[PDB]
Image (cartoon, rainbow, N blue to C red; front, side):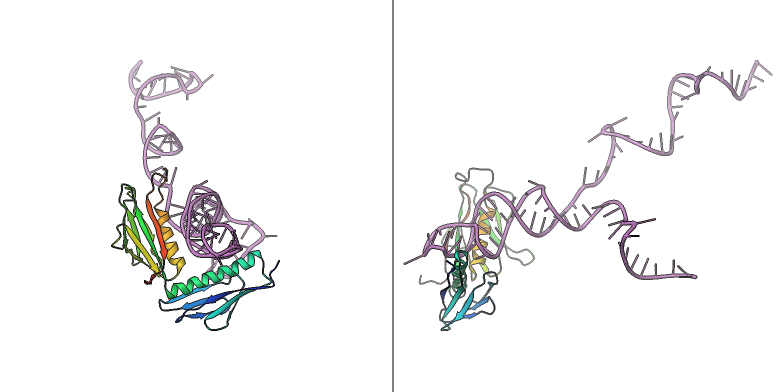
Length: 191
RNA sequence: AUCAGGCAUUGCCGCGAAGCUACCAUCCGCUGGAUUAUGGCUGAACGCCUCUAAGUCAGAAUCCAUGCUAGAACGCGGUGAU
C-alpha cells in the first residue's frame, strides 16, 4: 500500500530521561545510562508530553513499518533496562559429570571458567560483557544469574555461555547436558 | 738387470680424502582477521511465535592477511662521491 503515515507510542516512566538527536537514543534512569544509535532504520521521533514520544514512518511499506515497531521495541527495552533492568536465570543440567562453573580473572577481564563438562579436560572461557554481573545463586543448586541493564548484553552473555557447552558427535536427545536459560525476567521484586 | 716406468681406449683389484649427493643421512616448515554451512541473541512483521526483516553473536581444511619467493627491466625513495 505504501502507508502514507504510521507511528508507535513509546511510554516514558517517572524518573527516566530520553535524549534523541539524529538517531542516538540515550536513556538515563535509576539503574544507569544506556546508549543505542539507530542510524540504520530511517524513522522520526517526536516528544509530545515529555512522557510519551511518538516514533513515525512517512510513506511506509511492509518491510518499513515492521522496523518502526522494532525500534519502539528496542527503545522500550532500553527504558526497561534503566527502570527495572534484566536478569537471566540459567540451570546446570548434568546427567553424570557435574559442571564446575566459577568466575575467574585473567589480566582483570572477568571470565566464566567451565571445567568438567562431560568430564572434558578443556577449560571453557566465557568473557563476561561489561554491564553484565554474574551471581552463582544459592537456594537453587546448579544456578547462575546474569543481571544488568541492556537486554542485548545479558541475553548474548547467557547465549554465548549456553553455546560453548554443546555436546559434539552424540545423540543430543540422550546427552541432554549443558547450561540452559530457564527464566528471562526483571531484577526488581514485588513481581 | 736393479731402481723407476711405458702400453693394455681409465689394464684390473683394495682402500681412498675433497666435491656432489641419499626419507639410504640430517635439520626446518608461522598465527591473526573476515566469512560459509550451521547453531544462536534481540526482534517486528502476524497483540503470540520466530536466527532475519532492521541490527547482531558464534563459526570451516574456505577467503584475506602475518609470513615466505620475485621485484614492475617505462613504480619509487634516501644516501655517498661526482
